[PDB]
Amino acid sequence: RLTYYTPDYTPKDTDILAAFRVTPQPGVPFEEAAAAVAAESSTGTWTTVWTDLLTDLDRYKGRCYDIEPVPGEDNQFIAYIAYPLDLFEEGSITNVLTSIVGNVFGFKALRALRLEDIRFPVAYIKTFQGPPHGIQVERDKLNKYGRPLLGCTIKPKLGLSAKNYGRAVYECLRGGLDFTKDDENINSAPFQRWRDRFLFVADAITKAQAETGEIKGHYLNVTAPTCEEMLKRAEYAKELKQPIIMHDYLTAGFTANTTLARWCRDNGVLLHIHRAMHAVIDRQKNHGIHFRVLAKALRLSGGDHIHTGTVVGKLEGERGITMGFVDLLRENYVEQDKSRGIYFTQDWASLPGVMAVASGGIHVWHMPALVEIFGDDSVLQFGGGTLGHPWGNAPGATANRVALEACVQARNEGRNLAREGNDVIREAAKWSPELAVACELWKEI
Amino acid sequence: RLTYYTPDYTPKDTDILAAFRVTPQPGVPFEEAAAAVAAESSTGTWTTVWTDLLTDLDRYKGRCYDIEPVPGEDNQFIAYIAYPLDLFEEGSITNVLTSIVGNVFGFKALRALRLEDIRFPVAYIKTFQGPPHGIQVERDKLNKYGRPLLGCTIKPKLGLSAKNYGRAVYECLRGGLDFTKDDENINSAPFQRWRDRFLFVADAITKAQAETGEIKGHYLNVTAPTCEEMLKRAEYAKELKQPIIMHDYLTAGFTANTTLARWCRDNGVLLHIHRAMHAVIDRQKNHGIHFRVLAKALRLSGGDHIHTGTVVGKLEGERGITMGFVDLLRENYVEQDKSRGIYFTQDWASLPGVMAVASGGIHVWHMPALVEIFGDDSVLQFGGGTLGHPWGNAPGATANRVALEACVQARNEGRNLAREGNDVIREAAKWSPELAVACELWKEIKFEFEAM
Amino acid sequence: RLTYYTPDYTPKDTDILAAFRVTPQPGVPFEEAAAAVAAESSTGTWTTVWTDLLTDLDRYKGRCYDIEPVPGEDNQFIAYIAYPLDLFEEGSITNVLTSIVGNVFGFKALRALRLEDIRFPVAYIKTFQGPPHGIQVERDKLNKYGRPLLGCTIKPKLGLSAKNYGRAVYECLRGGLDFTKDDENINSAPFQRWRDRFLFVADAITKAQAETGEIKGHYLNVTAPTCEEMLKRAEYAKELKQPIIMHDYLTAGFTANTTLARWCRDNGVLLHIHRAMHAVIDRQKNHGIHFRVLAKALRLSGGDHIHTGTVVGKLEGERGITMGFVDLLRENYVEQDKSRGIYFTQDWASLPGVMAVASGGIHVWHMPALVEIFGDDSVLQFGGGTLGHPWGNAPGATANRVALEACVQARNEGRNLAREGNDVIREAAKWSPELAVACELWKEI
Amino acid sequence: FSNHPGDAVAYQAWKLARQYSDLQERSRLIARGLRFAHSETARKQIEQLLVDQRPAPIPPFFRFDTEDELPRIVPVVGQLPLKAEELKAVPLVEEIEPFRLVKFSGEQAWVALPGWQVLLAAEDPVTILATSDRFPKQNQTEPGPVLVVVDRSQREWNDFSYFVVDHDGELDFQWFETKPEFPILGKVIILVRPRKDSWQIDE
Amino acid sequence: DELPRIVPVVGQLPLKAEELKAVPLVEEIEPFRLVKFSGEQAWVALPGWQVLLAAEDPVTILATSDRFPKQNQTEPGPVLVVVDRSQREWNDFSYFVVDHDGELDFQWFETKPEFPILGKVIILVRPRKDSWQIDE
Amino acid sequence: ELAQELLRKLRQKQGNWVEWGQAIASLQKSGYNPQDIFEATGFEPVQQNQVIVGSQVYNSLEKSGASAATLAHYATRGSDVLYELRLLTHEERAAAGDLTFTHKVDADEAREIAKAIKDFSRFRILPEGFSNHPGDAVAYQAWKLARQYSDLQERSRLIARGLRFAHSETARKQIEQLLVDQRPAPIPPFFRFDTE
């Protein structure tokens, strides 16, 4: 009711700020739409009651302080809303979401609505643990420095016995990769049960780490129907003295994931986050929540890895948007840059950073690009698209470690991966026959 | 890769079936697009390897068995996909979502994608507790039969002291309503801390119940950052002999809700579910997940109440859709009706029904329609739009209770609430001064019938 | 070594700031002394090692950013030091003290040194629970609004049986006071054991609260040799469904008190804080820590009451210093005011406030002054000096409730307590014979 | 801006300073640009940012959208009843790239329809304005106006669709069980009939 | 969703002042928003961008992007330009069509009645496959 | 005794809040406790205290010469604001009320003003160039606090306040002096007679 549009107002260092992309109905003035979004996120439609005469509670009103139309676009604007610190429960992403994205998406007066970014103030951030361990601490724990880490996707996705899964894991670890992945779908099921898979994967890890002299790990999927069961599975991994587990934070949810993250710091286990069912919420440019927010939320409700997708098959425009939230995940201070889709300067208050996980149909030939774009603080997940290596998993692994070591060596010398990227691999393939069969199987780019 | 489109295959009584609304990119044939969702939701887009000797894993192949173009639409179809029973973890909505809606919504080859319905088979349903208590079981726990239950929204939404909230709750219950809601956003906060709120709300329910001689209850919000904390608050509610609690299931998440629902059966506390952040997923007709599915999901990961919004300022297309999922929440068997948006016949295998909760801009004049549309099995939540009662909350309660008794009484005689609905409340206002002030505070409405 | 004096530096909103009153030795330049205080509080004397060539850790240096000589005084200055947020453990006053007041008081190069104030930044404050309950919440719990609360000191201090203590408590509660006090010395002892006193005090409370229709409480002293025992005693009070307990936070210490404060919020029991052995640390104007800091520390490591002493026998200068830290305990924003001894603006970030407890040789005649100076949010502790009431404890209580109700009534009408203060009581004494015997026993002022 | 590192840093600071529309918020970034700029061409670009004499307003650009399809302009032969002759007379439309213009000299009526895949697929489309009772009654709804689009280049028979036919010098829509000798002038591809206190949340 | 709109096209710039003024106002015939016309004309169907739908009298002109200020690095290309003839009040934040001694051009002056505002520029628009891989 | 009229009117929200304050105080003095009053009427004991003391403050506004704009406004809002002025005397309240009403002061800001006025009233011999008008008292606070800051940017909040609040022209100068940063009279090196 236009008490919620106050453009004079300067937002405080303690306020939570939201940037919604508002697409109002034809004939709806922007000033009203904006004031509706602040009133429905913060306080509600205000219900005047006899109590208002005695004492006023207006300090807890959220409010639109700026209204900026989107150029290039159809009757569209960015509502910049500011909520005070006292609205929110300390350490609860669950509440943040409940208040900010709770009801406001269900108007009729808007055609559509999308939350693009949240400014988490330092004094709110300091109430979260954040990642169980940082980028830094993870490298310390694993003794892996100066390069991206390499992970493996087991195939086929589903239907394998626990012992088979574990044998498939052994090879791909034995052949030079650092991690292996439990497929997101894989929680306990009739074809394969969660304890048998944990035991045999731990067998595999032990043997593969013994034979190779490198710390190995597998992202054991503790995702589960209940908190009881999630933690039961966490605890068995901890009992098998495992380095890392995983959790589908969106499907399981934020209350559940925040529990697990803190458990992860308490027991010193790494937490690999999968983002299943993100595309339901973050694809449509007119309506939803940009992954950018979901990535910030996962940084606060803890994670040590997060799937960020890939930027190999995507154009220059999306590339910059992808590498914006990757910076929000990994860096301590991220400057406001609206060309990259970052609507506020995010200062993280020395909260640890999450490693970005790249995945898709990537294979040896993509290596130079991935090392170039992302950098060292990342995880590269192979075996994701229609791609096999005809000799096995361990030869397939060798091909990608040799390839990654080659590009990382090359980059450190001063070689240009942007232009010599393909040359570096063919040179590497001359001495490594595992990379030679790989190079011939996929066309370079 | 077109081994996932098999229209000659008849689906099994044990299969989980999905109804995706596929909107392929122009140029992309329906057959490929149908078989993309089958492969990218069920098993991997097959990655052929040297192990084709060991690996005849065709059994775990989800598949499209019918392809049905949506009439009245721009190059759009329903993919009916069938997944076998063994894919899913028992009693796990979290897995059901991870498997079905996990990655398939992030294609490029589709413009958009919306999951309209899921057929949960009987054999899979038997692996879920479902609601902590039925509709019937709830009405027996409370001694409340033959009518809708009445709830109250505390205002203002945010900022009240714990003690204030409790004084507010005391009245609204004292004045004749059954329940009082704790706001969804109200979890522990610097202006109001949870243990204080819970304590004073309990002081109120005790008193109001004693004075009235009706079982009163408040939806205490155990929604919280961690399972540790959520259960801590459930336990304090339980320690205060509380009849009912509430929980923001989508925001908190299914893992955390299923825990709470089971805890709720173990301690015999009623569970009031709030659907905050539904409109993010369930609004755009081309992309997301229909609330229908999120309603079915909440019936499996448990709940006793669920908000269904309102059906009063919405047209007869959308009414049929809203009363299709209110049928899915409350009934045992729900026949396939595609006009209503029910894509599959759903047999619930005696799983308890959830009470539908109506909330919106509703006030005393909406009563006749609400009683007519929903029926007895529902909770009517007042105080929600731009509406106050200028005497206080208890007066505002009395108005609604007197109003509801009037209509329920009237319908039971044989009176038509469709036409005489407004007369029934007018008649009621003659003797009740609280309803009189209310009736004159809001404009009434009469009858603007339907056609189909 | 003068890398720690950087007066150009502007302190950040996230920094912890300290104000030391430095009294250096003759011949010691102020610039060095200041830089020594920052180097010994923050980092230490810096030990150069071969590691310094590779990576530099200078961001964690504390530093003097301002140096202001004290006028009126002998070779004296205020060193304003700024430490970054990352130095400190979240929620630990124990650490704050360990870092800031840990070693720096033990120089030879300084004659003396005193910590006058700490600026706790909002983003550090939000990591503390603070008081278990606020001023506001406490009034809600007790149903006592619009006036100071009244407490009683049992006499004699020591030597009474548990049952005697409880009978003495019954009367003083029965006669109109809100609280009674366990003497600070009283933890379990041969003459009286902690469970017997808790049981009989709870008997007394019940009966006195039944007969009078007012919520009563007693500050049961859970102070104890161990954390185990402290909590054991907390738990029995909780089992006796008691409203309030007490704790000598300085003698027991901050690790112990922070445990108890959080236990107090968890179980909804009020926490009355005694400040025994403050005068050891906060009396001497040249050396120590000003109570101002200790009061801030108690606001963070939780408390619901705190003894602030009295301002009846103390001159205009100390009065303003006393009422500065009382404002730091009770208000949300306190403006920098150096005439009152407040060296930084303290913004509390909606942390609940502590009620100030006034005590000393106060009696009925002091009431007008106490109500005037402190206000409603306070607790008035009678029976502290060489003062008895010859009829009993319950008549003595009646005298002070009647007196307080009279002054509070008077103040609300618009009467001036500053000038009619004495008149208000004599008027009240005409109808209350308990106040009449009291008025005649102590000379007015 | 040159490829000197100092220029590259000044360019970053430049690009980032342009999104801020208030001069106080632009101070950190200008101060950096000046500290770092190596060429004099760059240092000017930075210096420009100090003014707040009004600039060249950014013109109202909208984007060629390849995300959604574009509309098609369709010719309208008039309201039924009509002669075979009047539908034969409307020429094939040539859309002039790059903006899909349509130029025409005689008398004509036009409509802009949405870009529906069927309509884009049509080689030669034409509009006819009729009533809904020209086709079978579908549901209970009363006969209303309908806009009918036909493809004249689709004249091959089938039993599942409707066609425009030359009914002895008259236009008519009918369907066929058995393939006819009656002239078919086109195939019906689209039928279309003609085309608020709610700030209330759907809770 | 939105209604697409048919808009008249006066020809390719360069053009004369009368040519634009010779184009009649379009009457959209309900219920299907038809447009009947007798003389020689050119047309385009655009989307129903809310600003266009708002325009009481719109007209299209085909010009190049270098007729306006250079926005980003991209080379001068073709642009379709829409103007509302019923918006002829001056302001400093938009472009107009003016009276350039026997024809018009597009200009950004803030105080100009001397040259007539024929119309206001509302729209500028430039002219208008192997992956099932998933965003994981 | 029909005293149910008070309750009925209180329950039905007849009249303004000052009426309510007086009604409740009449009921209170007539043998009702605050829980009784809450059961019968919607007013919490905390709200009962707010309006009883608020109405007492309102009595002091009209009995000590508040403007008719102030008494008209505080008739139907601002009980919270008037509760913060309870600390001030019968006489002090009327001017304070005017000031709070003029400046559109919320309860938090009212508390701050009441402190500044109460601070000032303890001075026997008034600070030079400041009257005992509440506006002066607030400007004096802002003055005193601005003098400890030695850099002009840190002095901006406090000057802006002093100007907003200063009532006499003698005070407004004192505030205006603070704007310079021509060097002043250096504070001479005073040491203290030490009785310590």
Image: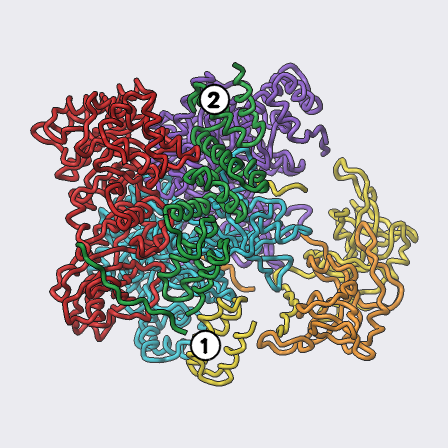
Chain colours: A cyan, B purple, C red, D yellow, E orange, F green
Subunit bearing disc 2: F
Q: Is residue C228 left or right of residue A298?
A: left
Disc ID at residue D33: 1
Image height of B293 relative to C438, above or below: below
Foreground mark, 2 or 1, reads 2
**How many numbered dots are placed on residues in this image?**
2
Marks 2 and 1, how far apart in space? 72 Å
Subunit bearing disc 1: D
Mark 1 element type: helix
Image height of C374 relative to C387, above or below: below
Disc ID at residue F27: 2
The residue type indicated by label 1 comes to Gly
Query: Looking at the picture, how far across and down is residue B182, in whole percent?
Result: 46, 34
Q: Residue at x 53, y 32 (%)?
A: F17
Q: Residue furthest front?
A: F125
Contact? badges 2 and 1 (CB < 8 Å): no
**Placement of the C terminus of chain D among the 4 image quadrants:** top right
Query: Looking at the picture, how far across and down is residue C70, in whole percent?
Result: 25, 63
The residue type indicated by label 2 comes to Leu
Image height of B100 relative to C6, above or below: above
